[PDB]
Length: 370
Length: 104
Length: 96
Length: 66
Ligand code: HEC
Ligand code: HEM
Ligand code: HEM
Ligand code: HEM
Ligand SMILES: C/C=C(C)/C=C/C=C/[C@H](OC)[C@@H](C)[C@@H](OC)[C@@H](C)CCc1oc2c(O)c(OC)cc(OC)c2c(=O)c1C
Image (cartoon, rainbow over all chains, first blue to last red; front, top):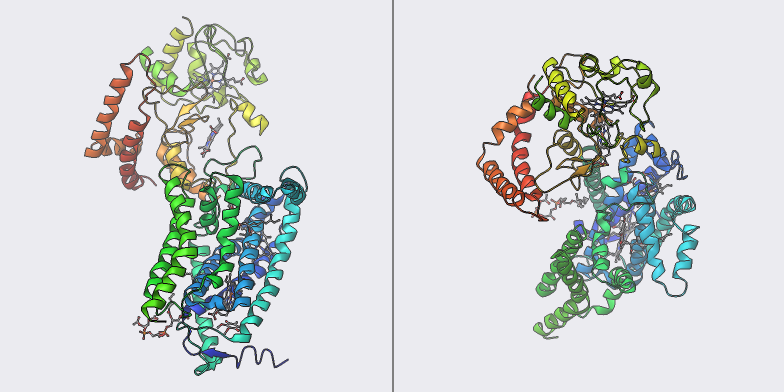
């Protein structure tokens, strides 16, 4: 019982200098536990039949004791999950943590699984966004030649999104988080083989400190800040990161005129929307996420971290600003000049990752004479 | 009553459910052409509530004065959704306009 | 809903339990809509059954102005002016 | 019984921005009203005016309500 709880926590060697950017791993663990705990309690009152799904959710928020806080904690917790996910990935790119190939690639799988999980959860209340989100996203599969359409109808359990869809989605959404938990434990096991990277990108074996009490207390402090952010949202602005259209029950005959994705999917939606071709947009969407698996092969710098690399830093923040641009564009109508800004931002995204950054890496190497 | 003031009241509070001219279409409410001198619920082609059809009074300046002050009170069960016009003068003006417009 | 539409020239009065959370602008939107009916501007002619309301999307709504001074009497004697009635129903809708 | 909305609207319509907008509105009313078959209408001019007047109403109105 002791060991592996311990030598896997208590006396785990850790760099003496990891910064707050290293707090997101434990914050993601906490977001996962939060979602699982609030999720199970919501599932104790939720019913997946299309005639009663939306109703069961209002019953939770209106009549179940504290049902409203559990619900908005689950909704806003999903948002916190993504904020942390994006900070976590950003930390990895900036500091070259991706060189831990197994840990990194498992991480890419984790990002995709959380996205799929959050997607399905959003469908459960069966409001307007639920219904059209289910329709659009499952249809991404229709871009697959020969069987695409068949795969979609098979997923739906029919010729359109209906009862069979909602009921299986409740089942998928229910189990996936536990699968995510098992995948995350594997994520950590591979990390433990190497231990953590640090802001300098330089091996920290000459200066390790025990995880307890240094990072246990630092992680607790981080956890408190996460809870503050979550509760500011739940108690003072529970709908801020939500969409008013989902307070309207699903209507299969009418897609809201200003329909837009959940904020954490806006950058990817902007990219897909920028290509006036079905298959092309779907491939660009898939690639906007999967390209993360290519980062390790695109590393040209002789140094692991961007800490000592000025040019790479500038390009890194341009990428972040660009994702911010795509997020903004994803929230705007498909009209001029947004159509062009979005296309440029989409091109700039792939250009920074595939060309500009690897190039900055080589130039910096030359400037240092190696 | 002042016919011009009544026209303004009709346009703002009645027109959306009633036409007054001969041949005017029925809408949420019945066309009102020929209103004065006719019994309640007798405009052909409109589905009145039994409450309205059974009131049994004759529309005129007097009955309209009371009805328009509080429709539901005068005809319990009516499906006409209108709170009523409180001011006596406003009702007088509106009725003066109706007397003219529903007879031209 | 079919019966509702039939009773309202084809338009559907939506359920109001969540109207404030189901509309951008919430009560600011609902208050503005209720107190913002006005004449169509020059060059705009609406089909019968529709009313001009600058705050409704497209500006043509199937709901006739529902409130006005003295539309009801309050239990506490508060003067029932259109704006007062609008302000209180909106507060109630927020709670709902 | 007077609705403070009436009073407040009257007061707010006195602001420079509201008068300017009302003028553009009447200019559009004149132009459109004067043409045989035109597709233009004064929606934009009316909304500009209302946006200016209602921003002012919102800051004063509730001060007279219960
Ligand atoms: C029937 C005679 C009505 C009365 C009384 C009121 N409303 Fe209504 N309302 C009605 C209809 C038929 C419609 C549909 C309009 C359309 O063109 O779709 C409406 C709509 C509304 C809305 C929704 C507006 C939107 O953005 O979609 C609201 C907010 C609204 N109505 C509010 C409301 C309130 C609070 C009322 C009492 C003061 C009220 N309505 C009366 C029909 C009728
Ligand atoms: C459910 C999702 C995830 C969980 C629970 C999780 C958890 C963790 C934990 C607990 C650590 C150690 C602490 C830290 O450095 O933050 C870690 C490290 C790491 N994670 Fe994740 N992670 C998640 C998603 C991802 C994603 C999406 C990526 C990247 C595509 C990723 C990449 C990494 C890498 C490379 C490290 C090493 C960090 C370093 O030492 O510099 N993780 N993660
Ligand atoms: C990675 C973890 C999870 C994520 C990211 C997630 C995400 C979501 C999202 C975005 C919604 C819609 C919220 C809304 O109503 O606006 C949702 C709903 C729901 N989730 Fe989760 N969820 C997670 C885990 C769980 C688990 C483990 C269960 C149950 C065992 C669960 C049960 C539910 C239920 C019942 C709903 C419907 C009620 C509601 O809408 O609040 N979730 N989830
Ligand atoms: C102040 C304005 C209004 C006036 C003076 C007015 C007058 C009348 C009169 C005199 C009748 C009886 C017709 C008959 O027996 O043949 C009537 C019926 C009716 N009105 Fe109005 N009306 C007004 C506004 C409205 C409005 C705003 C609505 C709708 C929301 C409405 C809906 C109806 C309906 C549905 C009936 C038939 C009711 C039934 O069969 O019970 N009226 N109205
Ligand atoms: C049975 C399980 C299935 C079929 C799971 C499939 C999962 C697919 C992906 O996750 C891995 C997917 C969620 C992820 O793509 C990487 C997102 C970034 C896609 C984002 C996304 O969202 C939208 C959305 O939310 C909407 O809401 C109302 C509406 C939308 O357009 C009208 C979109 C949309 O156009 C896109 C691209």
